[PDB]
Amino acid sequence: SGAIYVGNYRVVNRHLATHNDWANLVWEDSSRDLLVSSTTAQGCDTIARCDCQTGVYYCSSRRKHYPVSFSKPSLIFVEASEYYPARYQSHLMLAVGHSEPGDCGGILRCQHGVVGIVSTGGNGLVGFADVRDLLWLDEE
Ligand SMILES: CC(C)N1CCN(c2ncccn2)CC1
Ligand SMILES: [Zn+2]
Image 1 (cartoon, rainbow, N blue to C red):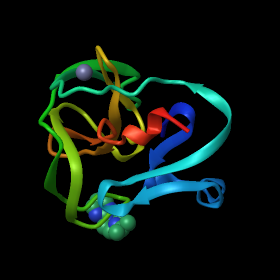
Image 2 (image 1 turned 60 degrees about the horizontal axis):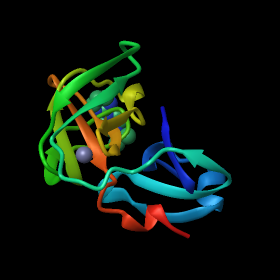
Image 3 (image 1 turned 180 degrees about the vertical axis):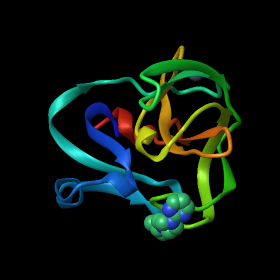
Image 4 (image 1 turned 120 degrees about the horizontal axis):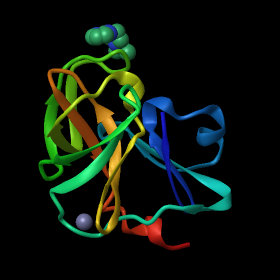
């Protein structure tokens, strides 16, 4: 579990979005595994605006933050998980590291701020849904 709290937006994995998220929906994309809802209180996070390929992510199934190198966001085939069938996921970055389903929502960050959230795992990789292209998160 986990979210990004930027301005008056909550960014969550689409598959973990709640009824309240859907009732306060700003934007969602199944192919990216993202959903954004509106918040009453302003949030503490800054979104990275960069093309970094190194950062640090939180792994809840280890209670640990790990430094990783990661691929640039791409359209990638993802094998079946507990929460999605085998399918193509867009705007996905991969690193070598540990990720189980409940790790979804952990933040990946670089020197510029939040890069994305854990969205995939298995086979010794962790996949992150990028948010650095979503420039509208920084205003309004
Ligand atoms: C949500 C649904 C599409 N899933 C969940 C069950 N399943 C699976 N596959 C691999 C590992 C664990 N569970 C495939 C079908
Ligand atoms: Zn960066």
